[PDB]
Length: 119
Ligand SMILES: *[C@@H]1O[C@H](CO)[C@@H](O)[C@H](O)[C@H]1NC(C)=O
Ligand SMILES: [Cl-]
Image (cartoon, rainbow, N blue to C red; front, side, top):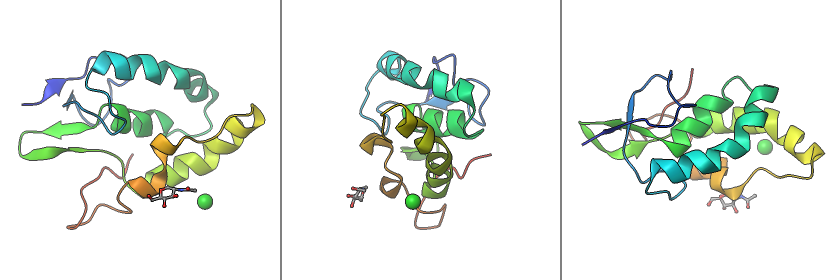
Protein backbone atom coordinates (compact mmCIF):
# COMPACT_ATOMS: atom_id res chain seq x y z
CA UNK A 1 0.00 0.00 0.00
CA UNK A 2 3.02 2.38 -0.01
CA UNK A 3 3.90 4.39 -3.14
CA UNK A 4 7.44 5.27 -4.31
CA UNK A 5 8.68 8.84 -3.77
CA UNK A 6 8.45 10.76 -7.07
CA UNK A 7 9.80 14.09 -5.74
CA UNK A 8 13.43 14.31 -6.92
CA UNK A 9 14.52 16.54 -4.01
CA UNK A 10 13.30 13.92 -1.47
CA UNK A 11 15.30 10.86 -2.65
CA UNK A 12 18.29 9.93 -0.45
CA UNK A 13 16.45 10.05 2.86
CA UNK A 14 16.11 7.22 5.38
CA UNK A 15 13.02 6.01 3.49
CA UNK A 16 11.87 5.21 -0.06
CA UNK A 17 8.08 5.28 -0.03
CA UNK A 18 5.06 7.41 0.87
CA UNK A 19 1.32 7.47 0.87
CA UNK A 20 -0.74 10.58 0.25
CA UNK A 21 -2.28 12.58 1.68
CA UNK A 22 0.60 14.32 3.45
CA UNK A 23 0.65 16.49 6.60
CA UNK A 24 -0.06 19.59 4.50
CA UNK A 25 -3.20 18.31 2.70
CA UNK A 26 -1.97 17.30 -0.76
CA UNK A 27 -3.49 14.17 -2.30
CA UNK A 28 -0.93 14.26 -5.13
CA UNK A 29 2.87 14.16 -4.88
CA UNK A 30 2.99 16.55 -7.85
CA UNK A 31 1.10 19.24 -5.87
CA UNK A 32 3.48 18.72 -2.96
CA UNK A 33 6.51 19.01 -5.27
CA UNK A 34 5.35 22.31 -6.77
CA UNK A 35 4.73 23.80 -3.31
CA UNK A 36 8.09 22.45 -2.06
CA UNK A 37 10.02 24.43 -4.71
CA UNK A 38 9.34 27.51 -2.57
CA UNK A 39 11.95 26.15 -0.14
CA UNK A 40 14.84 25.10 -2.42
CA UNK A 41 16.57 28.49 -2.03
CA UNK A 42 16.17 28.22 1.77
CA UNK A 43 17.63 24.71 1.49
CA UNK A 44 20.55 26.00 -0.62
CA UNK A 45 21.13 28.76 1.94
CA UNK A 46 21.82 26.10 4.58
CA UNK A 47 20.34 27.62 7.74
CA UNK A 48 19.75 24.05 8.94
CA UNK A 49 21.20 20.78 7.62
CA UNK A 50 17.96 19.10 8.78
CA UNK A 51 15.66 21.33 6.67
CA UNK A 52 15.47 19.05 3.62
CA UNK A 53 14.57 16.00 5.73
CA UNK A 54 12.05 17.95 7.82
CA UNK A 55 10.27 19.26 4.73
CA UNK A 56 10.29 15.89 2.99
CA UNK A 57 8.95 14.18 6.15
CA UNK A 58 6.03 16.64 6.02
CA UNK A 59 5.42 16.73 2.23
CA UNK A 60 6.07 13.04 1.64
CA UNK A 61 5.80 11.38 5.09
CA UNK A 62 7.26 7.91 5.59
CA UNK A 63 5.04 4.95 4.72
CA UNK A 64 5.41 1.38 5.98
CA UNK A 65 3.25 -1.67 5.28
CA UNK A 66 2.89 -2.42 9.01
CA UNK A 67 1.65 1.10 9.85
CA UNK A 68 -1.44 2.84 8.40
CA UNK A 69 -0.82 6.42 9.52
CA UNK A 70 1.81 8.44 7.69
CA UNK A 71 4.96 9.01 9.77
CA UNK A 72 6.15 12.62 9.82
CA UNK A 73 8.68 14.53 11.93
CA UNK A 74 8.93 14.77 15.70
CA UNK A 75 8.28 18.24 17.14
CA UNK A 76 11.85 18.56 18.45
CA UNK A 77 13.35 18.40 14.97
CA UNK A 78 10.77 20.92 13.76
CA UNK A 79 11.82 23.32 16.53
CA UNK A 80 15.52 22.83 15.78
CA UNK A 81 14.92 23.67 12.09
CA UNK A 82 12.53 26.56 12.82
CA UNK A 83 14.84 28.24 15.35
CA UNK A 84 17.67 28.33 12.78
CA UNK A 85 15.68 29.07 9.59
CA UNK A 86 12.86 31.40 10.76
CA UNK A 87 15.23 34.34 11.45
CA UNK A 88 16.39 34.10 7.82
CA UNK A 89 12.78 34.21 6.55
CA UNK A 90 12.03 37.25 8.74
CA UNK A 91 14.89 39.20 7.10
CA UNK A 92 12.93 38.92 3.83
CA UNK A 93 9.55 39.77 5.40
CA UNK A 94 8.47 36.11 5.55
CA UNK A 95 7.22 34.08 8.51
CA UNK A 96 7.37 30.43 9.55
CA UNK A 97 4.03 29.10 8.26
CA UNK A 98 1.21 27.58 10.33
CA UNK A 99 1.41 24.48 8.12
CA UNK A 100 4.79 23.76 9.80
CA UNK A 101 3.71 24.78 13.31
CA UNK A 102 5.89 22.57 15.52
CA UNK A 103 3.16 22.11 18.16
CA UNK A 104 1.09 20.17 15.58
CA UNK A 105 3.70 17.36 15.55
CA UNK A 106 4.35 14.85 18.37
CA UNK A 107 6.88 16.20 20.92
CA UNK A 108 9.03 13.04 20.75
CA UNK A 109 8.88 9.50 19.34
CA UNK A 110 7.09 7.56 22.10
CA UNK A 111 4.89 4.52 22.62
CA UNK A 112 2.21 7.24 22.66
CA UNK A 113 3.63 8.91 19.55
CA UNK A 114 5.12 7.73 16.26
CA UNK A 115 7.46 10.18 14.51
CA UNK A 116 10.86 10.49 12.83
CA UNK A 117 13.29 12.36 15.09
CA UNK A 118 15.66 13.12 12.18
CA UNK A 119 19.31 12.47 11.28
C1 LIG B 1 0.45 26.25 16.87
O1 LIG B 1 -0.47 25.21 17.17
C2 LIG B 1 -0.88 25.17 18.51
C3 LIG B 1 -1.54 23.83 18.79
O2 LIG B 1 -2.66 23.67 17.95
C4 LIG B 1 -1.83 26.34 18.68
O3 LIG B 1 -2.37 26.34 19.99
C5 LIG B 1 -1.06 27.63 18.46
O4 LIG B 1 -1.99 28.69 18.37
C6 LIG B 1 -0.14 27.62 17.22
N1 LIG B 1 0.91 28.58 17.51
C7 LIG B 1 0.70 29.90 17.54
C8 LIG B 1 1.88 30.77 17.87
O5 LIG B 1 -0.39 30.42 17.30
CL1 LIG C 1 10.48 29.04 20.35
